[PDB]
Image 1 (tube, each protein chain N blue to C red):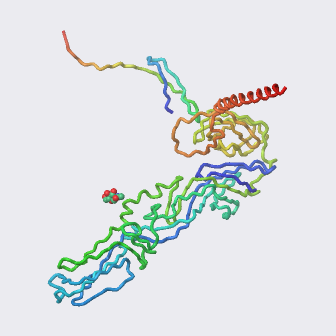
Image 2: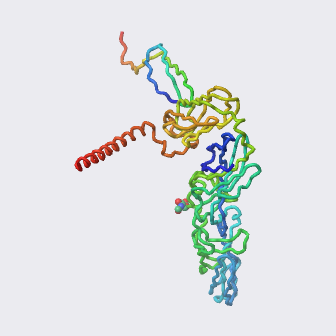
Image 3: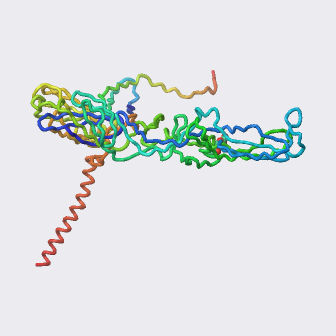
Length: 437
Length: 49
Ligand SMILES: *[C@@H]1O[C@H](CO)[C@@H](O)[C@H](O)[C@H]1NC(C)=O
């Protein structure tokens, strides 16, 4: 049987319902999401790390001109110096006094320690929500992993489940993300090839082992001044360490909606947001005939010491006049109160205690012991514990968040004002009819 | 649950209260005052004979 209903996406917090398929008995249905994996689609532009700036030996040649060539190496910088006369140890290196040519060559390379301390840059496109569902119907359980889009039921060995599109589309990732060492940051890195010096993305490559490495660090080769052979060069500071110095907090600690983000693959787990429209196809095997299911005649309610906390704060004694021994479900129709127990064992003329979690100051709700309806009506005290360590099982709806006596006084004032208005219009009508006569 | 309660400070005469949380059964708090020593701050100022 196709049953469609809106359920919370929050992890835990069981959602219970009943199906009424004519004369096939009220059949219970407990569903609860236990995992919520939000996996976006990522493409990789570049990986970056601290660079090394390997500088080869100078090419000095003595009484000649040695203009250099271009190269495909990362951030190749060449300069040619005249009028040099270098000293290595043990004496001079040119037989020429003043006519010499020194070649200074400086490209840049990944550090040997970039196998770990490397950050990849990604763009996420669309968040795909995959949720795992625990279902118990009657006495049959089912673990089903389903995508939340409206199609692809997936695992249908016994049960068919369609997860409709979610009410609110939430994505904890911004359009550009950076992953280093298992930590994700919502950073706006530059495009591939748009390398600026002193900031993130100064050196880029598609992969760590790729020879196609690009960089635009401000490396400048200086004119050699001292007698001894070397290269003088001034470089802009690597923007990778500057980004590490002021990365802010990673997205595992700043993500909204209370969910935690893991890498390989990049996903967000247990994101509690919105409501999932669910559509279940309950098999007819679990359905039983209403003649076999015991019926019920008279049901009375008495709930004592209600408290509208997040816990199951309330005990109701519930009296029945049973027709026949048997186990059969129980359910509270009002969304404001949810029952701990889903199926009781009703035999003959007993009192059943039930635990319910509510959010209204008034406990005025409809409950079905194994069929029919029952109006539980009493009052609920405020919680004494200010902060509880578990989430609320009922969301407020403002239809019952105002207390019964508060509706009484507020509606009494409204009724007084409206009654004065009605008396005013009535006496205007009477006076108009009198002056018309 | 923290239950504030006013008790007379007479020796003997057992005092009785009920503690209760809405999801729990009531329990019989039994409080008795046995001794009450009024020891003040005393300093010796002289001795005579
Ligand atoms: C960068 O590192 C230096 C070195 O100690 C530190 O003083 C500074 O607070 C860090 N952050 C910024 C934004 O300069």
